[PDB]
Length: 117
Ligand SMILES: CCOP(=S)(OCC)Oc1cnc2ccccc2n1
Image (cartoon, rainbow, N blue to C red; front, side, top):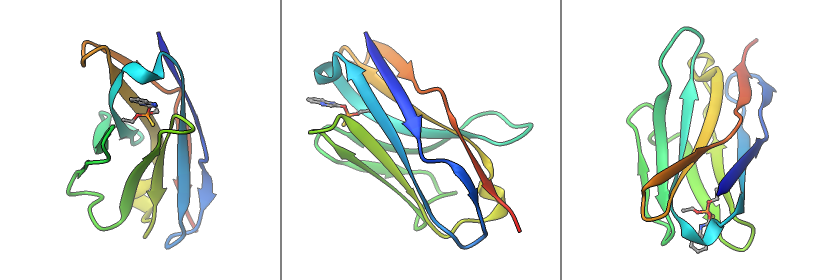
């Protein structure tokens, strides 16, 4: 059993920046990969980034050069550094973790990011 808790969203102006946290608890030593997803109003959830235990990162075209995913194994936390923020980045951001040799998956509760004014 792995649980994920998110924090760090909020309201920011276009051009601002935010860091989102994804704190994992439970059998975190079985986690294989972690990823960040977002769900815009009225849209399917969308893959954003992915990171392995070793630190290899993968990104979608929509956030390449603007968002950064990292992980701190000492704290069981995965971060999403959201920079160069556009109004189109307004969404609920979700983190996930694949564990037990990628057989199971856990999701965070989501955190709202609003880019306005
Ligand atoms: C949401 C938290 O994700 P992370 S930092 O994994 C990102 C891939 O979880 C952890 C934490 N400790 C670990 C120790 C050994 C092996 C894997 C671990 N994964």
